[PDB]
Length: 154
Length: 250
Image (cartoon, rainbow over all chains, first blue to last red; front, side, top):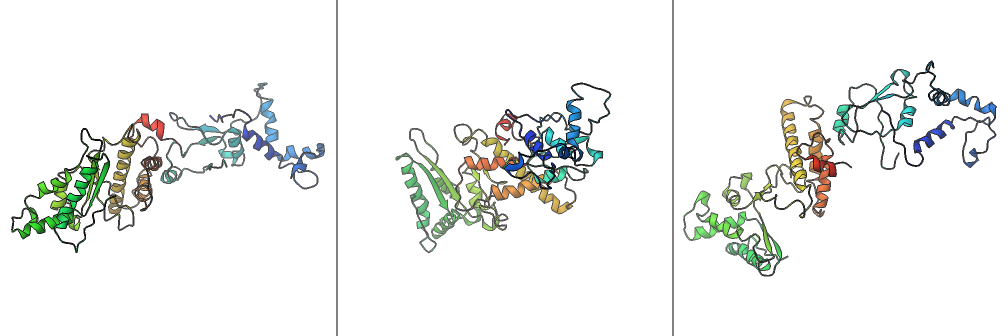
């Protein structure tokens, strides 16, 4: 259900996700990639080998580009806990703020026990633009992820 | 603007002939000079205090509550000099302004001016005591000719459905706060507080105006439409779907 709409042109959430993984790229100097001198580092096997150790998703994403088109069914991975299941009630045409690379980002930092199903609790374009509806739909429903987008696309 | 002032220290007979100067000027500007005239007759209750004072001088008979017998045909001598005519391109609109004594609507000046005219506005006291301007009570206010003033060609095609939906979510909101004071605060469900979020935002964004803020009709409905988005789409049942699918989502 998480079909985040691709943009004609480049998807802007592919771009800002990919540079996040390169923030954990700790060069041997101890100082992070800062300024326009971040393009010219002789990054040998000494420095990429902790990057695949620190970042789990660059180790995860290679196991789904290879082992899903090639269709090896014996694979002992979990795809229920990588991408959650979008549970909205039917009948209501509802697009979300968050596309699939974003909901694969927030789902990584949750507890592991909850990562399989994201159910709709409140949304401003379906349940009104009221705080009395917000406080009535999200009270007493367990742990939930509030996510909002202002006028400046933040 | 022509301004016919008439003070309280001025004689009592000049107050009788004042609303017949203001209409003879109006029946000239619209039915001979082809203008759209609006007549404002401030404190028409003091007209009926002078018409009682003139008639008592002639030792005449008093009718209901001291006012003369001929007061129903003497208020209609003023009010029925209005309306559009055939042939001329002018019209006269009248807004008389009264004072109900001790807030009793059953007084003969409001009871007989509601027999000849076509609505009320009801400036309310309970909205003035909570510092709202203009304190207009929309629950007893009416205009019997609203259907021939709005719609396509006049204002916009969503006017007749925004208006009687705001009137329904202000009517329910006045019931919730009337009932929540008598039964208690913990009986409100989550849909029930929503008719109180409207009621507070209706009295601050729609009824509160400020005495020099001139809104056109296109920015009263665009104020009114962002107040109907407080509710979800399934709860607006006074509004049809063919106009909900054009104006509601933003």
